[PDB]
Amino acid sequence: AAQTNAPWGLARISSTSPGTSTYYYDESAGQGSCVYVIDTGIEASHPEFEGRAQMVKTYYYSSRDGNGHGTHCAGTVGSRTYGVAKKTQLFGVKVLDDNGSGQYSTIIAGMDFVASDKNNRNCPKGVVASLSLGGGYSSSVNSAAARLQSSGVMVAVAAGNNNADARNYSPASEPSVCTVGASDRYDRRSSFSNYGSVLDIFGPGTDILSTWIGGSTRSISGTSMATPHVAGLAAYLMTLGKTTAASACRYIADTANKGDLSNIPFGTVNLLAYNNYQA
Ligand SMILES: [Ca+2]
Ligand SMILES: [Ca+2]
View (spheres, helix red, strand yellow):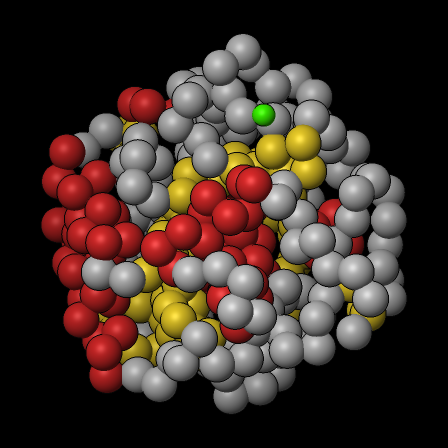
């Protein structure tokens, strides 16, 4: 398959060079895979999801996404125009309120929930979880993200938008999960991107066009927008039988784009997510 005039983030994942505008992906598009989107929830009624998005849990009182953050990142995972795993099943767990805030107890309970409701769903190819939140260091949310990864889920988390070492932030500094940095249009490190040895992979995170609440589309930039690129890539890769949730992150790093990024500090990886699809 091939999508013309794609968002720069989609085309970059299917490329060895920046600047391309066509996104090349296998026709499977990650069908049979599930990606839990742990954010502000998802607006399931968006025409870009096509019944593939679903609100399965809210830790507030309404499954609405009255923020737009969670609908944007879920769009990058597997919507029609802006998703990398265009046929995946999107499950929306709402740990962030309509302001983008969220207590660690709520974020932890959301990860503990995904690991259980995973067994109540039909995901033959496997399960993915994209946690594009980020707070200060916590031993317990690092522990909760590891429990999600150990339970059989590919866990992609945001590196943080602090321009510092991601070792001070959670769940980013959890070694078991996949910490995703953000890159911009020209294969530079995003000016907000966290770095450090904790990061496992980079993704398009600057000016990422995706869906938005109210049936709209808009671009926002953050490592929280680069994370869904790796979530959908892991989903799209596990559908191909190329990798397993337990090692999707390491497989993406093995088959990434080596040394293409600039502004990478010393000790941080220089890998850009690459689906390696060749038609
Ligand atoms: Ca998001
Ligand atoms: Ca490297």
